[PDB]
Image 1: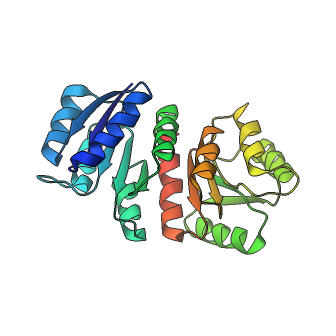
Image 2: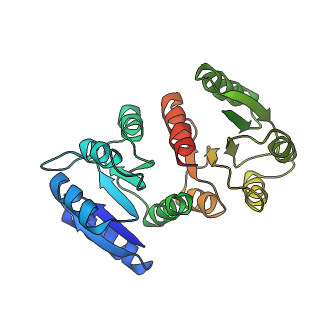
Length: 118
Length: 118
């Protein structure tokens, strides 16, 4: 399956890409909101890992515009960890929300759980 | 929709029941693993909130036996918060895993996210 990793930090994108690759996923990456939407239309990923904090267009808007056309599972990832952040992420259409820093194993498990359910 | 709350602590069951009721869910409760499986068969809940730590049969076994027959969404809830706990919960079939103590608003949001997806 194909995962789109949307993260404006290259070190973190690289770590997620490495671990998702190691599991047998095809990985596409985007580094801002605009690239996220372009990659989403062009690549039709099976799941999207989406950070809230993005150049050009923020993660919340990315998720909101994606949901206008698609039920693709979205796992939001963010260093922001307050109740409000988690709640608004999910209500705007994320299927899950994981905080940074994260466990690589938990992330893999959550990606699988999401894929199992769509 | 109907939520089965499986929790061996009555104060916590009561809080979840209160807040899920306030949202318009029908609530059924179980206080151990055996009651969980009985309520699951008899009531056919739309979602199950399941703590790991249960009398008679533990939460991990509850989730594992449920999955033999049912794709019903399971949200695991536990004071245990390590990587291992979260990972094994999810791999044994939970759709999500939230730690105690939890935000009532985040829990509501996660229940909705799960229901949206099944």
